Image 1 (cartoon, rainbow, N blue to C red):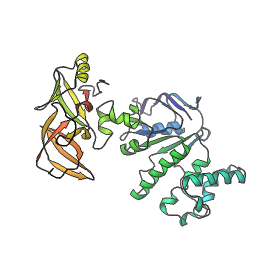
Image 2: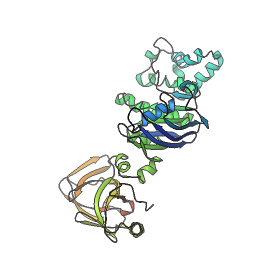
Image 3: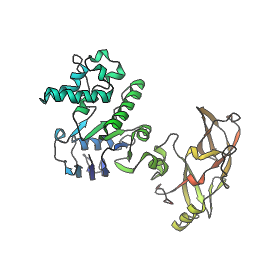
Length: 366
């Protein structure tokens, strides 16, 4: 289904809204992740969508029908993780069928939908077992079949991995991804975990304090963050940020001076940033081990002291600074590199971003 949120607001007791002008158009088959820190308003928004909470202002549409006034049960939404407990004395089959039985659906049609769900969950050999005979990993899949047999237009998932242990969490995460690949049901998934957002979504809605910060594919949000908060929240280790003073062709950070690409320089000039203090952002992977990288970087190298060098698989995380401004670089593993040495690094200024010092909003050079 297509969903439209048109200028939605939620207010409680205080006159600052908990959700502020939430505007979004979700296409069919998208897996949309709402992500942000504590109090971002994602979970409230999801419950407004479910119809557990009332919309204060604006319109919510499902397939172009305004459903603000429609009761939860009539919205054709499945709250996938609600009433999730299994009946211990019923089979897998019966735990998945239960809601259809209550609905008096004919037995054969029940059978057809149940078997189909079991195949999608990988439970076809287990249909006549009891829950106790399934492992923990298999057992947590069963109640998803209740959502699939419902034949709903949209699935809602509110932070379903948050209370699971590590081993069950990895398996649920994977199950959710598969369920989206096999059924393609339009889904809204709320989390506080930016890695889940990057790896599970078709598109992400980054939220803070009830306000949409950015909407985009995971790659778009990562590569072109709207502001400094998004740049710092998405990615781990997240973007490095520096204060410097822009001149004609150079950004001077502490006692370093990095050449700014002409293309970017032109726009910054035209927007009137020459001679002003600006925030410069650059990802760890875009700070290169200058020795090794095949590319030549034109006057954007510095000598950095290695505070710590941490091997992580085939990469090294380097913790350093430009004067008093800390940064992390993420380079390919090499052996000489040791905590305490010096290392020349080259900033890829084609991947650098500039943000306004007062607004923290990214300055569109693209």
